[PDB]
Amino acid sequence: KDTDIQGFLKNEKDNALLSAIEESRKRTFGMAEEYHRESMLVEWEQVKQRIL
Amino acid sequence: ATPLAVNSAASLWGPYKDIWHKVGNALWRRQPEAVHLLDKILKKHKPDFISLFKNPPKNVQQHEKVQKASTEGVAIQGQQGTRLLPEQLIKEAFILSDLFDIGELAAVELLLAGEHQQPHFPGLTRGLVAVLLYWDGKRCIANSLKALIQSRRGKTWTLELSPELASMTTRFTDELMEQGLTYKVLTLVSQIDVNNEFEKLQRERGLGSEKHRKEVSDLIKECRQSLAESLFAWACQSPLGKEDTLLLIGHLERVTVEANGSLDAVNLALLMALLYCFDISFIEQSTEERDDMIHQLPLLTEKQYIATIHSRLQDSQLWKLPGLQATVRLAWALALRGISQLPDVTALAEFTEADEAMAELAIADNVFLFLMESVVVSEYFYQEEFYIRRVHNLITDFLALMPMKVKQLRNRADEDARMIHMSMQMGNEPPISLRRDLEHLMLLIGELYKKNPFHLELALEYWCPTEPLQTPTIMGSYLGVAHQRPPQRQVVLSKFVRQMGDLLPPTIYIPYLKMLQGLANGPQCAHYCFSLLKVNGSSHVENIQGAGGSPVSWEHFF
Amino acid sequence: VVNIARYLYHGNTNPELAFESAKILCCISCNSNIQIKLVGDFTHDQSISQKLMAGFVECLDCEDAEEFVRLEEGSELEKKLVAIRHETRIHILNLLITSLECNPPNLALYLLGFELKKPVSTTNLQDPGVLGCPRTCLHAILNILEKGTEGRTGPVAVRESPQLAELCYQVIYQLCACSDTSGPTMRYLRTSQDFLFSQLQYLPFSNKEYEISMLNQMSWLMKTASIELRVTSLNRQRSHTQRLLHLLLDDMPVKPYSDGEGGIEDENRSVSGFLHFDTATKVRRKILNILDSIDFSQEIPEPLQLDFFDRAQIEQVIANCEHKNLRGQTVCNVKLLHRVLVAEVNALQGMAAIGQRPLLMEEISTVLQYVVGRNKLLQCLHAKRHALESWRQLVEIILTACPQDLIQAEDRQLIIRDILQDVHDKILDDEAAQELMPVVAGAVFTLTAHLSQAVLTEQKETSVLGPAEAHYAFMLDSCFTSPPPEENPLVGFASIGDSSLYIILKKLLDFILKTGGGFQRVRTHLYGSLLYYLQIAQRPDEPDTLEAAKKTMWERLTAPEDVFSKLQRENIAIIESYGAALMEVVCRDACDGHEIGRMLALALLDRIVSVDKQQQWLLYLSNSGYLKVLVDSLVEDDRTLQSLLTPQPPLLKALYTYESKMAFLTRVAK
């Protein structure tokens, strides 16, 4: 309810705890694709001079 | 910052409760911030106390504005502008104006208070509530007056009030007594009657429900009572003046009992005020404040006080109640009996040589019967302690200071008992003109100490320890008070209880058992009475033919 | 029952009949089944109903105070009659309190003046006499708290009847927390009495006798003020929201109306003070001054010592007496405990027991006094915690429900930075009661989240001013005096470098260490707080522009450091300064802790291994073996994750903990 304060000041804290975990996880997992891509591009950024 | 301070003598309730609550916080709650308000409130409302319960008067220059209040309007304190008043409130204001003899703006400001307070009295009207507020406003003045008198310095109590507060209250209320306070109070207490005010209120329909009739009936009694008690609370702390005591006598001349035989709480308080104007017993008690307690007595400094009061009490004019005149005659005879035992007081001998004669008049007017049936039988006699203390003194000082009258009363009782015995041996009724002086005194003692609403064991003056109590259960002191001798008052009184047991005739027997019943009231009182009834039996050993043990003993009874 | 209730119409003339009447009616009002019928029999006859309403009000508006029961000068009979009248008020307030949590229609909604011939939420409450409105128990409960609201001393009942004031504030809380009373009540309390402003100005309340009751009075007044900040904000009633915010938040000394011509004397106070002109006297905010009056320490009564009774049995006889009172609180029934211990001091047939009986009653007296101490302790630990919960509720509505255009991006941050530092020290002190820690960490979490959210608006709305147009704006307002030096206008953003933010980091790590391993719900809030704090130190996502990719390796090494790169260095150096103790506390709770404990401690290790440039935490994680406990456990996670592939999975928790374990491993592996 809406005069109900303790249901609200519970739920937005369970939401805030999940949100603090969520950007840690999803920023680290996006940083997994980007780390393979930069590593692929940096070993390629060795190979073309081994070639040239 | 002007003008607005002009209406502020018309509202007949709000300013009076504003005084009463702040007198309550400054006195009974001792609150220090309220002292710096009380000084200013007493300086403001001194005119109101100088003319107790007096209305603001009617005025054509209010009457116009109330009749025009539907078109020109009225300005009211706390409100910005003029309020237009309905024809109803205008006509209600003229009804309250002629019902109470109040000014037309005061009837409006009282109806505006009655309109604001109406929701607290569900089922009444602002007019029926204005009838409450007009008597509660008077009650707030009367209770403030009583509390401002109880907070004087004086000879009977000290409410811990600061030496400044206790001199502010004293001085401010001396500055009301200057003004003939006793005359104003006795005028109000003899003009205010519930029946006359209910006749006014029933005609013009100012009586509501059965609760409202109870409320108005009691607010009018509180207005009589706190006024009469203002003279009692004065007289106990500081005695009334010469003409004031003659006005108080001049009122008591004219009293009548209620339909049961007792005084009302109001004329009881006025009797007790006159009795405290005649107390001197503290001069057998105080040693170091003593001489300033003596200068504070018209009974010692005004030879004129005694000369006028003694004259009006030796007077052959009977009062409406001869037993009330008898009670005041006994108190005056005992006041003279205290004064005749103070050393240098030779200057009053021409009045004190009458002490046993003023006592014979009090006995002849039948004082002890009126003290029983018109004073001690009242439920209001057992609602105040200083009433009980004063009727204790009025009997103990008769027994201690007039033991030659006590002997005259026994010489009579042991002969009117012989008249009753001889009539019954002749087969004839006892003659109606025999006098019950000692029977009435012993029944009065038996009906007095019979209740003790403040636990005081005052009957202990009628006892005296023959054996030491050995209660081992209090361990809190080291002051070895070596063997104090019992006081002469107690040594005469505890002798009187024993010597009215000497050879009891059958007429005094039941009065003596009742005298012992009243004096057996309290834990020690009962133990000393048990010990008397034991000692009265423990003498008849071996002599089982000489029938003559005490008929007031345990062994005779069982 | 109606003729029992008619004795209340005689409360001034027979208080001993009105007392037992109110008390019988309080016992019967406990029955929720009977409430609906009492409303019938009490309103079917309006002539009786007007006497019933009058009798309940007549007992409440009576003026007699708790003082006259203590003054030794008074008559036994007067002391008794004042105590009877005061119990008569208390049983009327208890009758109302129990009736208000019974479903409508109930006896309290009648006695308080609600329109029980409509839906309750459509009630048009008004002042007594207005349109012919009767005086009701609501206008009496207000009158009890209204007396003294002009005074420099505050409300009269808070001093002269503190138990009456506690119950009066509870009825006003129930009338504002229930949905269908709240609309009528939260209108009326503002339209006619301004009641929440005229009372909150007198916080905190203060007497050393009635601490428990004053903490409960303040608890209920903070819980009504809470609802009005939310209600005014949702209804966009800006001026009333803002006026209640100022009364709680300003660093300003609220001056009473200072009319003229009064002052002097008090030149008595100790001349030695004339050299301690202490400019440390900051005007601390009203909401902090209420946190000051909530004590966090606690008196623990000394452990019972006994010569005759076994304490290992007495502690069980005490536990068998620890029932729940009408406030839900566990308390020992002293009258049952006394009956039981006296029964054994009757059952001891012995020569010897009947010589020892005085000493057995004397040791019963010390046991009963210790149990009265235990009952004070439990009620004080309740009241401190209930007040801290009410204060926390008020703070969190100011943060979650009040508009951002009523507390600005710098003052909102200062208020949270100061509240965090004050809320920390009262739990970092070692006398501080552990029962408060679940409320304190539960507040520090919402505070650190709102500090992080405020910086996470400030960063983005400052990210608008291009350094090319300001040079024209400065060229008009031609005032003419004394020039300043060449100082640079970059002020508010420098506050991301405070000592306050480094103090808040330490105090949070100190409280993470101090919270013992049973306090797992306290630690999940504190690990959440440290994640939100480490989001203040978060660089945002920058755009992969074909122009940012032109910035050379020289520009990427000769630019000044941005404040987030600085703040990351100084925060990791603070985290390093706790070393192996903080490393054990986080790594162990990541392996072994609660479902949510492991989940958050793994996200905290992911965030720490995102800033550790020395590999100290990685070298701890490997040489402790915790980096293998967080790997061998994948073969035990799996069995739970298999169950989460069912169509209706029982609890997604184990997935969310696996995703943070795998995030931590996918941080370490870089």
Image (spheres, coloured by chain):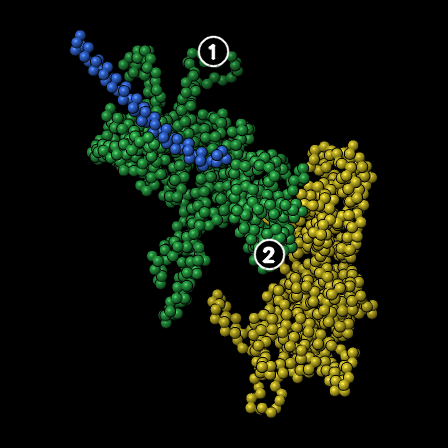
User: Mark 1, chain letter?
Assistant: C
Q: Name the residue under label 1.
A: C472
Q: Using the rendered view, name the quadrant where residue C623 is placed.
A: top left
Indicate the secondary structure of the residue bearing disc 2. helix
Whether residue B227 appears in this view of the structure is: no
Taking the spot 71% from the left edge, 45% from the top edge, the residue there is B124
Q: Using the rendered view, name the quadrant where residue C451 is placed.
A: top left
Q: Where is residue C574 in the image (x, y as percent from the top left)?
A: 31, 31
Q: Position of residue C501 (x, y in %)?
A: 37, 30
Q: How many C-alpha atoms fall within 10 Å of the one at disc 1: few (<14), some, or many (≥20)? A: few
The image quadrant where one finds the C terminus of chain C is top left
Q: Name the residue under label 2.
A: C16
Indicate the secondary structure of the residue bearing disc 1. helix
Specify the amino acid type for callout 2: Glu
Specify the amino acid type for callout 1: Tyr
According to the rendering, which colour does chain B have?
A: yellow
